Amino acid sequence: GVFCYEDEATSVIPPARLFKSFVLDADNLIPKVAPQHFTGAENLEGNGGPGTIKKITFAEGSEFKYMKHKVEEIDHANFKYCYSIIEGGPLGHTLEKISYEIKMAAAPHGGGSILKITSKYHTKGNASISEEEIKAGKEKAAGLFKAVEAYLLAHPDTYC
């Protein structure tokens, strides 16, 4: 089924403004810091909210990426977001999805916010990914999530 990893971070900004940087743009938000990983994603179907479908595609100076995307929920009373890659191209023969779940909370005394990002790899049962590979796949996203946060730490007036 799944293998699941977390990171925890903070923002200076109160949680709801960060929540919209994922709930809109999570698939584009790595590309906001580093478009070499994707030319982000374009919305194929749905009004932008829960259950919206995207295509994640290309890269800066290259055609590489081609993945289906779905929004899986918005839990806005809890400030938790779910979205997936539905597989596509390189990963797709051994993987069934990548799914991510993103949480914002207030900082318990910080006045800004706590950020959680959780990555889930979903597998094909007879073709399942190794644990060392799943740590490396999570780490490539995690350095980029640290990098967009590092841009926000250089520009605290911008919600990413």
Image (spheres, grey):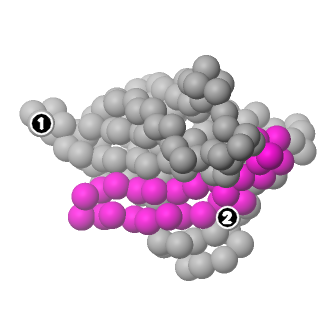
Q: Is residue 113 left or right of residue 120?
A: left
The answer to whether the residue labelled 2 contacts the one labelled 1, judged by CB atoms less than 8 Å apart, is no
What residue span does the magenta drawing correspond to? Answer: 68-93
Name the residue type under label 1: Pro
Task: Kindly report the distance in space between the C-alpha atoms of the residues bearing marks 2 and 1.
Answer: 35 Å
Q: In this rendering, is residue 145 above or below 13?
A: above
Task: Say which residue appears at 76% left-offset and 34% top-offset.
Answer: 36
What is the number of the mark on residue 54?
2
Taking the image as drawn, is residue 28 in sight? no
Tell me, yes or no, whether the highlighted magenta stretch contains residue 87: yes
Name the residue type under label 2: Lys
Q: Is residue 33 left or right of residue 8?
A: right
Q: Residue 80's x, y, as percent? A: 34, 55
Q: Nearer the viewer, residue 5 or 19?
A: 5
Residue found at the far front of this picture: 126
Q: Could you tell which of marks 2 and 1 lies nearer the N-terminus?
A: 2
Q: Residue 135's x, y, as percent? A: 56, 24
Q: Which residue is mark 1?
A: 108
Q: Residue 142's x, y, as percent? A: 53, 28
Q: In this rendering, is residue 34 above or below 69?
A: above
The 10 Å Cα crowd at callout 1, few under 14, some 14 to 19, many 20 or more, is few
Circle 1 SS class: loop
Q: Is residue 154 left or right of residue 53?
A: left
Q: Nearer the viewer, residue 124 or 30?
A: 124
